[PDB]
């Protein structure tokens, strides 16, 4: 189609998985969302980083292992977490995305430049280190780069990992879940990776039915904050903290109505 | 081949095809006789060789124009309109619509009201900006298309374009009535396999809105054709209005 | 709370159950919704739909249970042609009293005869209004308290497994969230035979409805949430319709209504 | 009684200690990371406390502290005037200094706040002129923590109070509110006070009806001890006054 519906959605109503293997360009995605001055995208990124900073450095969400689900090609969402977690596992469905991440982990000269984001977080954190040291500390924290599929009851396949203290997921489950029972199942699937009492940290868009990568359109599940809270509690978690902001992406990039952050814990049997 | 289609999809005797036809007849009865879809001119698009989709409509439209891509299909229509002995036997279908209508009428009266209402039998192509070519027609109250556009459009942009082309035959505020297959990529006539656009309901909604219509009513049923004839997963019916 | 939020919702965010005993006035509700207008058009569509379901589509059997009847009976008129026995239910005792008055043809009851005449016209004028009303009155065997949020929605009252469960404009008002809604559909499933029919009609994307100046909570679901909830509850949808007609702005903020017919799955 | 309140609510590893730390972290975020800043902040229902102005004084040149109770204001002024009978806020002052990067130590922070507070006034949020006859220039930000729940006997009064507060604000100025959710009472020693048990949706409806657009809204589940209040969590919001 030609913008009539999201790519890979004509038959099913929702962007198929294969669309993320064929048409998700990580370089274009990074160029569009993480790369002029005080744009909507810039403001959203600052708010995300401030929240991750507050969750991981001021609120002391911490432990041995953190798993980042649906990382895409980005690493901004780990910069503060690596201060509180000894080991980070990064995951995405897209092999293209895993490639971009591993290039950045190798500090390949062709990889995306996160320096401005890194400097921002370092300044949030008090300027105790400069950018380079913060980047290398994250590179060292990232122990595994893995394929994942949230809709599967073992989201990482037969890949054995110790139970994690935290699962983080930014801007992923909306794009990954074609309906609210799938969403809830995905949250339950993520639960299989968590220690009892582990932390679930989700950031995503509210009421977004698509997002753009340039002229390429991808489905989003348009959930309100009540639907998100419902799904999280049904999936077996208790919510400690739940926030909404009005700031939205530019219309040329998504039709979201704000974003949410939440911190939850996996309940008892 | 028009008769082969009639034999396979409108055979009589229970069957998935019987059930689909009955639900088609009941939705059109609802649209044209209980609901307020009426007017002076109705145009049916992609009629093929069939008349079942006109049985309730002729109760509400003074004049009807039947169109299709295949002249061979239109010859088959005309055999029934001229009541040739070999023409397809639609009386069990005429009977079932009459009973839906309260047996207000009997078969023969129903068949003659349809023959009188059908005023023109035209060649058409939904992908052209003028779907009827240089044949002029007054602006129509209603355009009707059953099981046509999925077969006619090889992709979703064409589908949207077709809906706009059809709109050019429609007054502002006129009715668009469409019934078609959902998620069907092929349908069979004998062992001849034809292509279909396998679109879901969200894509239909998106195409209709984008072509300049607002949807009044949209229904989907789960009943499909049997495996030997099409791989659809249900059917939709919708009634839309042409925006200004 | 002075309209700022629905009555009974200030603490929880959703109209409490007790509010339906205190503040839901049957006669006011009937005057407001069931007396052209957006409300009349909606009623006409509901009646044409119930006509198609029970008379043309052959949805039929021994026992139908109507859930959340309120004080109304329009939703049973076509049904009593296809069902030997009808059981009506509502959470509100005031509603049940209004129904009992109409069932005994109390002279002070609400007059359904124009609605009755309309349905007799839909059905072919085979009979006139009075005969049809008396067929319905004889068909209604029980009037029962119900609470859709409890796993036995009719409590300990024994009934044979029903052939159909009908629910018009109720579940939205009754369920404060998606999980209660899906659980309520499961509860309703307990009253149905396997392969039994579930027929729901309700508003789309409605967060409140008005009776005069009284504001009641509604659960604002879209068509995909509804389809998802029904399927998780153990049903398979046979047909699902949406219409764009909504209540006038002073009554509710809905964006259309839906109708569906479903069947309780094999186990 | 203002000193009993202070000893009970703001003196180690308890539900109250947890709530206070959440309040300070959110105040720090709003005023030092989010860039809520300007000329004049008006603190509404301050009681005898100052913790809620520690971060704010970094971003506003002038602060006005207000309360319904004269006793509360005299307790507060005892701290502004560095009287020896004042509550010792130093553990709290230290925590905020630690939140801000230890750019300063306490005594500097303490002095920064004392010269920012320009007036100590009476206020009643239910009156259309909450500060009575005292004229103030239009404020950039109105801050109220744990006040409105205690002050309003019902939701319409809650909403009216929020409009009254807006009469002090410039159009496009900030409203910053933190309060209890679903609390009907709170305890000061043996003495029981009444609270409006608002849910979060009621808070949002009241705020928008009073003529603000909400930029962010956060709820936390953490509650006071049962011996203190029967709240079920807390909320924070930052809203803008519409024109
Ligand atoms: N909702 C929106 O409107 C919306 C608005 C703006 C931006 C985005 C980004 C959407 N995008 C994620 C950004 C990545 C990074 N964490 C970040 O914060 O920027 C979607 C990601 O989800 C993965 N994904 C797909 N299906 C998956 C599956 N079944 N199992 C596991 N993973 C899956 C895709 O690989 C892709 O990395 C969505
Ligand atoms: N999708 C399916 O799974 C599917 C399932 C079951 C059956 C069918 C048959 C589809 N077929 C017949 C329907 C006829 C009649 N209205 C009826 O309800 O039976 C489609 C008709 O559409 C015409 N047509 C082609 N291209 C055209 C064009 N460009 N411009 C205008 N017209 C065009 C063909 O001549 C043919 O008459 C498809
Ligand atoms: N969604 C809307 O915007 C909306 C818009 C317009 C009108 C309405 C009416 C909503 N209202 C009346 C429908 C009555 C009748 N069947 C009819 O179609 O008119 C809902 C009925 O649901 C009952 N009910 C409450 N809680 C219950 C419980 N826990 N268990 C069982 N039952 C319960 C109430 O007593 C009330 O009779 C809602
Ligand atoms: N809700 C709860 O469960 C709850 C839980 C725990 C604690 C509290 C305390 C409630 N109480 C103290 C907050 C003080 C300080 N800002 C702080 O964050 O500690 C509220 C203050 O609000 C003032 N106040 C009353 N009516 C007023 C009016 N009409 N106009 C203006 N002002 C008014 C009273 O003088 C009192 O100082 C309530």
Image: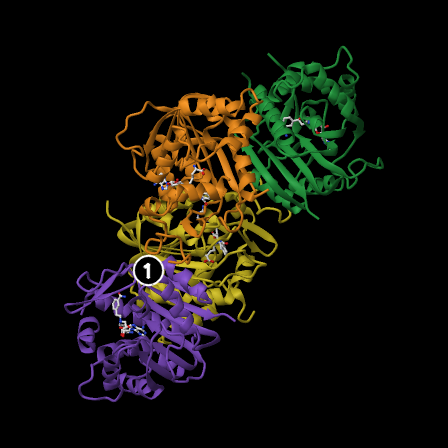
Chain colours: A yellow, B green, C orange, D purple
Of the pair B113 and C7, the residue shown nearer to us = C7
Q: Which residue does the numbered mark 1 point to in the structure image?
A: D198
- Which of B142/B5 is in front? B142
Identify whether B213 is placed above or below B236. below
State the residue in front, C36 or B66: C36
Q: Give me the chain letter of mark 1.
A: D
Q: Quadrant of residue D27?
A: bottom left
- Of residues A197 and D226, the one nearer the viewer is D226
- Residue D128 is drawn in which quadrant? bottom left
State which image quarter holds ligand 4: bottom left
Decide if residue C149 is on the left or right side of residue B43.
Answer: left
SS of the residue under disc 1: loop
The answer to which quarter of the image holds residue C142 is top left
| Residue behind label 1 places its C-beta within 8 angstroms of ligand 4 | no
The percent coordinates of residue A90 (x first, y second) are 40, 55
Residue at point 64% right, 14% down? B92
**Quadrant in which the N terminus of chain C appears:** bottom left
Q: Residue furthest right?
A: B134
Label 1 Cα neighbours within 10 Å, binned few <14 / some 14-19 / many ≥20: many
Q: Is residue C99 visible?
A: yes
In the picture, measured across the screen, residue A141 lies left or right of residue D243, that is left
- Residue C163, image x and y in percent? 40, 23
On-image quarter of the C terminus of chain C: top left
Q: Position of residue A152 (x, y in %)?
A: 40, 41
Residue placed farthest to the front in the image? C107
Residue A93 seen in the figure:
no
Specify whether C123 is left or right of C145: right
* Vertical order, C51 against B164 (above or below): above
């Amino acid at each position: 189609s030609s913008g009539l519906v999201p790519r890979g959605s004509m038959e099913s109503g929702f962007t198929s998985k294969d669309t993320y293997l064929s048409h998700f360009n990580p370089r274009d995605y990074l160029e569009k969302y993480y790369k002029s001055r005080h744009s909507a995208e810039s403001q959203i990124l600052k708010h995300l980083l401030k929240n991750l900073f507050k969750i991981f450095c001021l609120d002391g969400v911490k432990g041995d292992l953190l798993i980042d689900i649906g990382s895409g090609p980005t690493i901004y969402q780990l910069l503060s977490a690596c201060e509180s977690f000894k080991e980070i596992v990064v995951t995405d469905y897209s092999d293209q995305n895993l490639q971009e991440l591993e290039k950045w982990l190798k500090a390949a000269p062709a990889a995306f430049d996160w320096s401005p984001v890194v400097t921002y977080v370092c300044d949030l954190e008090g300027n105790r280190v400069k950018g380079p040291e913060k980047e290398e500390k994250l590179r060292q924290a990232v122990k595994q780069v893995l394929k994942c599929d949230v809709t599967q009851s073992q989201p990482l396949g037969a890949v054995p990992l110790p139970p994690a203290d935290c699962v983080l997921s930014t801007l992923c489950l909306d794009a990954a879940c074609p309906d609210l029972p799938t969403y809830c199942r995905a949250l339950r699937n993520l639960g299989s990776l968590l220690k009892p009492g582990g932390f679930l940290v989700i950031m995503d868009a509210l009421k977004s039915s698509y997002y753009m990568i340039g002229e390429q359109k991808f489905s989003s599940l348009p959930l309100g904050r009540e639907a998100v809270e419902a799904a999280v509690k049904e999936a077996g978690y208790t919510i400690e903290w739940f926030e909404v902001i009005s700031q939205s992406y530019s219309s040329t990039m998504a039709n979201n109505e704000g974003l949410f952050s939440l911190v939850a814990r996996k309940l008892s049997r």
